[PDB]
Amino acid sequence: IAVGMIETLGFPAVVEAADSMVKAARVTLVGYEKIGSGRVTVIVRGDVSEVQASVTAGIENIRRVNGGEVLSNHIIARPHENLEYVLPIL
Amino acid sequence: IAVGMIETLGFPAVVEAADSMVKAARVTLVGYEKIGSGRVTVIVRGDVSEVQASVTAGIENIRRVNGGEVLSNHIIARPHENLEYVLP
Amino acid sequence: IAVGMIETLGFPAVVEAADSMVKAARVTLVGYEKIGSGRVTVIVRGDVSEVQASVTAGIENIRRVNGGEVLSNHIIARPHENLEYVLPIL
Amino acid sequence: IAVGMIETLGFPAVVEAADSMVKAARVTLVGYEKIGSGRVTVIVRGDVSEVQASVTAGIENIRRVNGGEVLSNHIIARPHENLEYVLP
Amino acid sequence: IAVGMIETLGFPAVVEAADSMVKAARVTLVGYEKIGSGRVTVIVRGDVSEVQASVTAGIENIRRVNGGEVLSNHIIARPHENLEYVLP
Amino acid sequence: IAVGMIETLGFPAVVEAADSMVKAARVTLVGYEKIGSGRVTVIVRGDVSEVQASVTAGIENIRRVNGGEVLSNHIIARPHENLEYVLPIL
């Protein structure tokens, strides 16, 4: 099951990404990650095509947020088992 | 009901944000979030029109803080059941 | 009861602010807040006129500190009850 | 056996780094380290040639992340017994 | 008695700060504070003239650290009873 | 017993420093310190001459690291007892 994530400069933007993502498709919102410098990441899990739907919707909708910026985004279709317990993507 | 947040550079302005929001309308201050880089967020819940009125008041009144700066603001009208896994 | 706060770039400066504040008037020094980027805030509680006396003395006296800067400052005379338990101003 | 790490600006790229490493060769993802300033590191163990293969794959594939950036990469061939006091 | 602090960019210089302060005069190292952004502070207690002598020694000797930088220094002569709510 | 330390911009570099240090001489590697802005410090303890051997090797070998930088470094030959329990150098 695929993992999708959107990284924002700012917190209100990550919440809108999160919201848009879980409304747009069949994905489980599996938390968010803070790494400093105002960089925050929301992460979801589901079918690869649902996760694409989610990420696209998430990026689009930070245009709605006043002062929002997407810094990065990515999808992995077939994430290796080892990552589940090292990284906070579960 | 909706959720309303204002992010600021600097803590004193975020306290004004919070104070003005909760005084302006029928919303509950439910959240304070720090993400580093001096970026702080204040989060409220209540009817979408009460949330609209509070965020507006918060952004205006931060102009009254010496050294205050708003970085971002946002409202979400019908927040998803499971959005609580990113709120504090 | 009113809340006053002074935000500094730097730690030695926030301690001088804190000291000046609590000497200048009848206020309780109710801790300090760190938010990253070297931004730190001291907070006090008391009568509105005491808090004013305190913040004025606090800002003045970071001139004494070598390398000190005030980044922001603010006072709220009648802070809403809700903020007491969400924000670290108690 | 060796240790292999790739540091990135931004978390999504560091997940790709990890994924690509572990898929490329016979290495075990053993570590994820944050030092602030948006700087994140991913750490693997295994034979030096497997490690070499993994790190190389990780650096290439981060080019495929929208907003991805590699900050630093390194391999240590015969890491000291007591290096575990800085690994996570 | 007074309180003496030296803030530095970088941890190694703050260790020198500390070492020099405590060796220079009759003061006790009571505090080490991190506020992010690489900013670190070292805090001492003792007579105002011992504190004056220590801070001075600390500022001089950081010049001897490769990559050392002082960001700010300060002394408070008669620190308030309740200043301990901001000291570590 | 002397204390030596190397500060890096970046984590992979601090590990190479740490490794080189403990291979080059009789020193105990006594952890590392993070202070923000991507600034990390490795710390060791041993004879003054061993610590010098270690720091020299440490600084040299971050040339091996792709993207590595040393920001600062220092040695104290006879560190004051008071520092042991205030600072994380033990």
Image: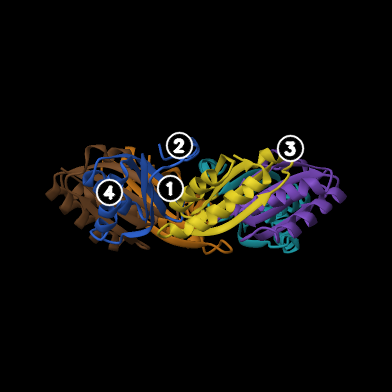
Chain colours: A purple, B yellow, C blue, D cyan, E brown, F orange
Q: Report the front residue among D79 and E33.
A: E33
Q: Residue at x 50, y 48 (%)?
A: B20
Residue at which label 3 appears = B81
Query: Spatial distance from mark 1 to mark 3, Cα to Cα?
Result: 32 Å
Q: Position of residue D55 (x, y in %)?
A: 69, 56
Q: Which mark is residue C84?
A: 2
The local crowd at label 1, few if under 14, some if 14 to 19, many if 20 or more residues have their Cα within 10 Å, is many
- Identity of the amino acid at label 3? Glu
Instruction: Report the mark closest to the observer, 1 or 4.
Output: 4
Image quarter of the C terminus of chain B? top right
Q: CA distance from mark 2 to mark 3?
A: 27 Å
Amino acid under label 4? Ser
* Chain on which label 1 sits: C
Do discs 1 and 4 share a chain?
yes
Badge 2 sits on which subunit?
C
- Residue under label 4: C54
On the same chain: label 1 and label 3? Answer: no
Q: Which mark sits nearer the N-terminus, 4 or 2?
A: 4
Q: Quick one: label 2, few (<14), some, or many (20+) residues within 10 Å?
A: few
Q: Disc 2 residue type?
A: Glu
User: Mark 4 and mark 3 in contact (Cβ < 8 Å)?
Assistant: no
What secondary structure is found at the residue carrying circle 2? Answer: helix
